[PDB]
Length: 55
Length: 55
Image 1 (cartoon, one colour):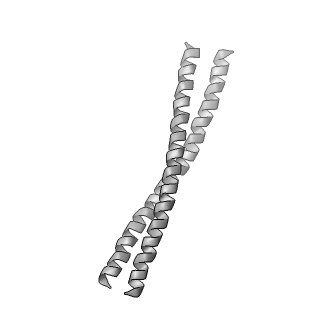
Image 2 (cartoon, helix red, strand yellow; image 1 turned 180 degrees about the horizontal axis):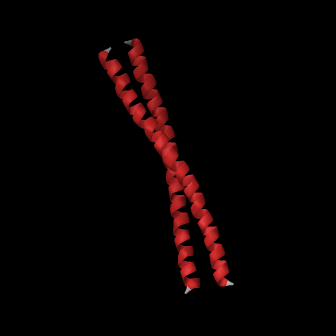
Image 3 (cartoon, rainbow over the protein chains, first blue to last red; image 1 turned 180 degrees about the vertical axis):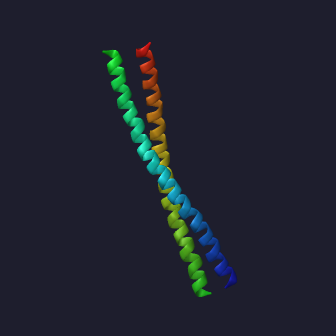
């Protein structure tokens, strides 16, 4: 029981780490969804600056 | 004990679910990170293009 609970606790420990990582990574993903979009926007804003400078 | 083992399995189960969800967001993060990277690479190419056009 103690080891089964220990496993539940170790698994809970890992779970919490994974949960924290899931949120951290998901939140970093969201940051990167937004950043990938901001960089995409920079690609377009830059294309417009290129177009402006091109004109 | 049966419950503790069950909890070890449920928490391990959840860990595995989180590992798959974490890998899913981590891999999707790699995709978004890579997209951010690609968008940043293109952004830099465009900045470089701005520099070319600016020059």
